Length: 220
Image 1 (cartoon, rainbow, N blue to C red):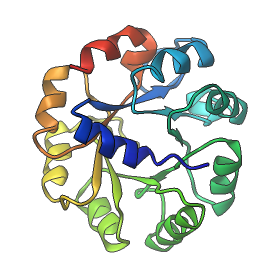
Image 2: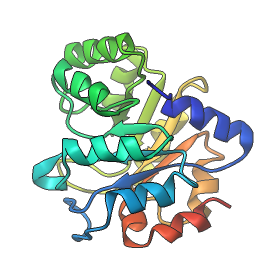
Image 3: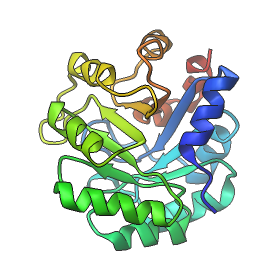
Image 4: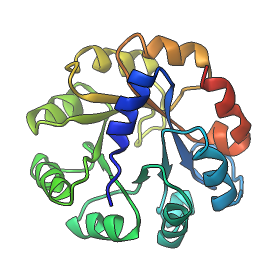
């Protein structure tokens, strides 16, 4: 069932180990196309990662519901179907596939849809990672009572990485919400930095698909 990605993140926080959410994306609107083995990668990362973020987004991220399905089988660490969740059914697929949580992007969702999509995620026992980009997504995640927020430094619409803005939000986020700082994390230097800023987990992907061995240096 649902192995809270956030709880593990919480245990990693107590455990002092860098809670990093490893992403698996062969294709991406940002990075280059790097085909790897879904199982080799997941296998190598379940040995270190706090969880895996998997992109079942076929078009722009070249990922499948089967990839997610297979990855979830192969590992005993939390999984996050990272898609563009807009319908409660995706939560179902998500759940029935192997997700232990799902990605909700405040941008593309009305406050109503996000609020319910959250409610329906919790009905399944999962705590969706709610991704925010600005002062306005933050205030909504907050307004719907989010407990697991994801501050994306990378803008969907533009692909621009405002780390400055990213950290602002992190400052405006209550110390009870598990914060996952996504995008842009390149070094263990910034990790321990954001980590001082309260972020509990880090969603990395492209660097890890490039050279997964890299996570070994992040976890220090």
